[PDB]
Length: 220
Ligand SMILES: [Ca+2]
Ligand SMILES: [Mn+2]
Ligand SMILES: [Mn+2]
Image (cartoon, rainbow, N blue to C red; front, side):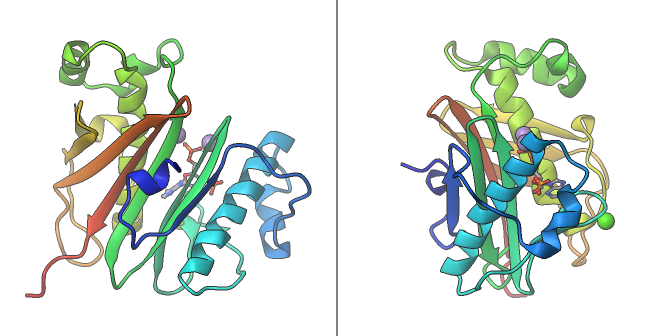
């Protein structure tokens, strides 16, 4: 009953854990990326990359470092796209081949009200009204935040540009899907235009998981 596997296609292997296994180490090449980090950050980085390597192995890729660009993005092997996420109680990764999909993003958040002031900072005025109308019993504010982070993680590998919280309007459906409508220039590095993403979401084990897969376009 893994959360990521419930919201991504079977051809994108994923792996997740809810605690840090004792005794894990980063690969030597990864050490500089966390040398200056506090212990809690070191731990989540080590465990999430353990998960990423598990998923990469399903695609036939043996142990390899997963470095980080200046903008925080993971640096995957040739022919691979992927995404990683962590919060207290979760570490998870998903990967796929570039011959199968264009991009993936995931994000995991505790299923709790957002911290004070965060909703006001991340939601467009219309989004605020939309969330207030969704059915009682789900922290739609936290879901919106989670979906916005996933939107950026799917966007950056295709554009090399920032996407602020105000730059996409996310509409959440109670049925486990959402849509992200881009409000800024959507030109992508492959010469296409990104205007909207389709997302999926699930709540289980006290957690929200959101995911976006950006499909390849049909042969022209
Ligand atoms: Ca960079
Ligand atoms: Mn995190
Ligand atoms: Mn997050």
